[PDB]
Amino acid sequence: TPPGVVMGLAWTAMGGSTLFVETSLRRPQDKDAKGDKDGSLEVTGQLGEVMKESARIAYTFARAFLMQHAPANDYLVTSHIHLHVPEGATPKDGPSAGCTIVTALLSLAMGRPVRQNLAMTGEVSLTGKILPVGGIKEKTIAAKRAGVTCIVLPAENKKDFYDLAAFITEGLEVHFVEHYREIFDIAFP
Amino acid sequence: RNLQKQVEKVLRKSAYKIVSGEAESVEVTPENLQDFVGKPVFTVERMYDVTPPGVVMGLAWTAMGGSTLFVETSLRRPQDKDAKGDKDGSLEVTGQLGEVMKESARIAYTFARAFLMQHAPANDYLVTSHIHLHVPEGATPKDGPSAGCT
């Protein structure tokens, strides 16, 4: 999964899935070296508008996190970026993958890949407040066959993860979280 | 309702422990409860302690009882790209707003920057800095505007 591409879980109406997510720069960086102009997103992936807003709010939270984090870098403020969300999630579970995008853009910023074969899901709110998500079972069995090493899950959901049949959980490392900054503290030691 | 069920499960597993279990008398206790209902569902009491800049608890009368939505907003862009260039920093409200909320939020922003100069002329942070805004969905269509005070 080189930079700007990541696998992603989805709770399909039939079983789980690990659809990927992709992001890319969309225009030359230096059309105007001084130009003060938005690095506008252009999302795609047969999104319903309920998603199309959510990608945007996530976008704003990413750009906020980044500007809070790395003042010298100005990448994200100014360059067009196209983004793809492959079909497959059951719609009620669609927003749940928002964080992966939030992480994708960051990888596209640093140009440094995530820790490998690190599936992750869970809804997020605008200050990185991870929220509990359902369907841990199907997501787990899908990941088990996907080479996953280190799932990260809502800190409010661990019990449900611990309600699953024993042999399933063997192997993979897990992490529980509330603030997204933790995830950013995992992927980049 | 949901507590009704969540009791029925307790009594039911308690029956199973009688007809074949060892103790003749269940004496449920808060600590004993795991055996009968398992691990907790709700652990965070409120969603979280307020983030100082951009949240205020907002009560709302959704279809099934009231709820304390948070509302989250953020500066949408660097503030000092142009200390002199003069363009408004508009909101982008979201959250599957109803049209009345559209009008409501527009009024709120304009009154907001009207207030900021009304009382703190030297400050200009809101009149000339970008803003994303997000009212959560959930509110009854009629009460949507009632969040506007927050």
Image (tube, coloured by chain):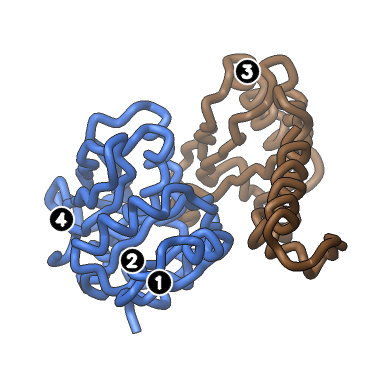
Chain colours: A blue, B brown
Q: CA distance from mark 1 to mark 3?
A: 38 Å
Label at residue A30: 4
Answer left or right for A88 relative to B13: left
Q: Given this view, does label 2 or label 4 mark the residue nearer the observer?
A: 2
Q: Which residue is mark 3?
A: B103
Query: For mark 1, does the 10 Å Cα neighbourhood hold few (<14), some (14 to 19), or many (20 or more) residues?
Result: few
Res. B111 image quadrant: top right
Label at residue A168: 2
Q: Are marks 2 and 4 in contact (CB under 8 Å)?
A: no
Res. B27 image quadrant: bottom right
Q: Given this view, does label 2 or label 1 mark the residue nearer the observer?
A: 2
Q: Given this view, does label 3 or label 4 mark the residue nearer the observer?
A: 3
Q: CA distance from mark 4 to mark 1?
A: 29 Å
Q: Position of residue A102 (x, y in %)?
A: 36, 56
Are both tags, 3 and 4, on one chain? Answer: no
The chain that hosts pointer 1 is A
Q: CA distance from mark 2 to mark 4?
A: 50 Å
